[PDB]
Length: 502
Ligand SMILES: O=P(O)(O)O[C@@H]1[C@H](O)[C@H](O)[C@@H](OP(=O)(O)O)[C@H](OP(=O)(O)O)[C@H]1O
Image (cartoon, rainbow, N blue to C red; front, side, top):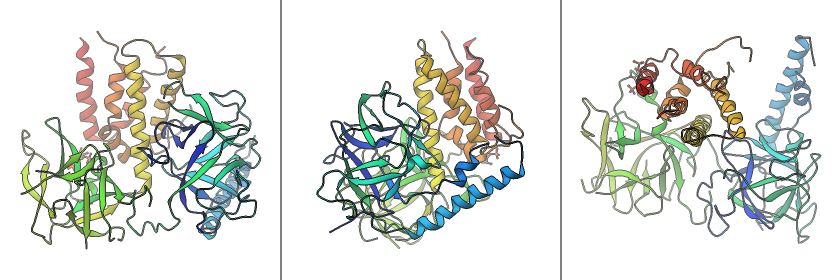
């Protein structure tokens, strides 16, 4: 019939006493859950981009595990030991590419890679779980290890070991050595209607719901869920979505640089929706979800004009393309109205020499009004993500301590976070006993444009114990303004509202 393969991207739907898709709480918190009322089979989850896993072959963790004994006075042995762990780490890559597309058989030993987080689902053999007492702590480690090996074995005996894994099949994922099989909990988390998944012998069956077949040539083809910017040919501007006069507007943004492709911005990024029937994987139609906010793109009331819509369902949010390949230069057409996108010069307004030029549409098909489908790096997408996290972590904490007390569990994570931010913004140099400390521009223009910095200030403040909070945030500030003349101006203005207490 139809089988599962190495490379297929699927979701895993629990079918025990608790049901749900496995998912993360983000790129800050390394825990795995089934949010049961978030989505079923019939009604798929809202942020279903987070319940997607790739099926990976068995990874090699021998020389890499050796190297994780940094028990040594000697340096050359350490450089010896690492060189292996890097050779091995690349030997995996070589081989896993060969095993691409091969049918998984029951009782092979695959790893399950989380797409959105890019971490490996992992049993930690020598731990308790956090919410459940007996069960082992299943986490998401980045590089993986021996406890990320899983025997994929059949739940009901309708099929058996050796037999090829068909789509939909209920399986038990069982760790190779790490002990007990994966199990979706009966315990809701303290903070989130979210059940903690862990490793303990229980009668949970995992439904394998295929999303995208192992045929997604990239970066080679535009397919659903790619993140791209839409640059303008003639106007030389990126399609952007932000607010003006408290109103969300879609526009081409005016730049003041000597390079048009350099004007890169997070608010310019869009997720692709290669429209399907069942929620799954050049002749059919597309919807553009604004990677920052979550709202989609549509043209309503030139007969029409492009603006954001809060939900991507209405037949307005759907577009068509005209000359699919990566980095294509297309002319896009609005379906429900049959019109060709067009850019204007009347901007939005109160500003002196503004930047937000309005975009509408026209029944006349042009030639110059072409948009470049500039592919965004997957890493950059995760930077928006690992930063959006920081905004909502401090979103709760700076709200929680602004009107009372926080728990002893919260300090330990925000202090952790404010350490992670230091490790991020300097492109993984700084952190403690340092050696060097040199900044990163992407993350800077991201500390700001995603309001990490806005949070920091609305955190320090207790208006009308800290030895590792303030001025820890101020060391983060100290980093994010480095040689950055625009961020300097921002932190100077933000410090203007900060002193306003007196
Ligand atoms: O180097 P400076 O003079 O301090 O200012 C930077 C740059 O020269 C532009 O003014 C601006 O890009 P735009 O022209 O596109 O606004 C940019 O913002 P960005 O780096 O956040 O894009 C600033 O950081």
